[PDB]
Amino acid sequence: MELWLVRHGETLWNREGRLLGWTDLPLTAEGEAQARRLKGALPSLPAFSSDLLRARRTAELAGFSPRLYPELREIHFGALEGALWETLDPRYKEALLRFQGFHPPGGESLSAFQERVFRFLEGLKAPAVLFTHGGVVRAVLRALGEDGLVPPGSAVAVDWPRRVLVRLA
């Protein structure tokens, strides 16, 4: 089934290479500009969005009226929220780059995170546009034999659960 996965527009932390999970950062002015550029470029399918501000706002500026679901949230980084990637302990840095065996203290394990993501996709009955986060898009791409840290403000279409269709940046 055609699913479009859209990563929220830029926030400050995205520029500054900071871990951003459940911290509810707003879009920057450029992030709003990115979201507005998506309007009309994405098919007007029914929309769903993470309930975090930057996802909700991206959906709105993109011309959608999404239903909110906490299952589309980015992974919770717990004590690592806002952690500087530069000084991130090597054990976490390695786990993230590899996207496996990662469980930030006080936050969500990669396994719990991916389970809620894939189980949300399980409930979709028709093609939809999902406003969500980089970790969610990466979980899907990796399962489909590809990878990618898609930029903020961009989207990927996939034929769940079979293959990736197109990356729109």
Image (cartoon, helix red, strand yellow):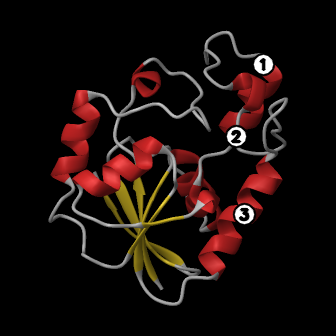
Relative height, residue 107 to residue 148 (above, below): above
Q: Does residue 35 appear to the left or right of 10 in the view shown?
A: left
Pointer 3 or 2: first along the chain: 2
Image quadrant where residue 46 sits: bottom left
Q: Describe the element under mark 3 as helix, strand or loop.
A: helix
| Three-letter amino acid code of the residue under disc 1 | Pro
Q: Residues within 10 Å of mark 1 (few under 14, many from 20)?
A: few
**Can you give x and y, in whole percent of width and height, for residue 72 in the image?**
58, 59
Image quadrant where residue 15 sits: top left
Numbered circle sitting on residue 116? 3
Q: Describe the element under mark 2 as helix, strand or loop.
A: loop
Q: Name the residue tied to disc 1.
A: 90
Q: Does residue 140 appear to the left or right of 157 in the view shown?
A: right
Relative height, residue 164 to residue 89 (above, below): below
Labels 3 & 1 near each other (Cβ < 8 A): no
Q: Residue at x 18, y 59 (%)?
A: 39
Relative height, residue 121 to residue 36 (above, below): below
Q: Residues within 10 Å of mark 3 (few under 14, many from 20)?
A: some
| Three-letter amino acid code of the residue under disc 3 | Arg
**Can you give x and y, in whole percent of width and height, for residue 70 in the image?**
61, 58
Q: Residues within 10 Å of mark 2 (few under 14, many from 20)?
A: many
Image quadrant where residue 113 sits: bottom right
Depth check: 81 or 15 in front? 81
Pointer 3 or 1: first along the chain: 1
**Can you give x and y, in whole percent of width and height, for residue 1 in the image?**
48, 86
Numbered circle sitting on residue 76? 2
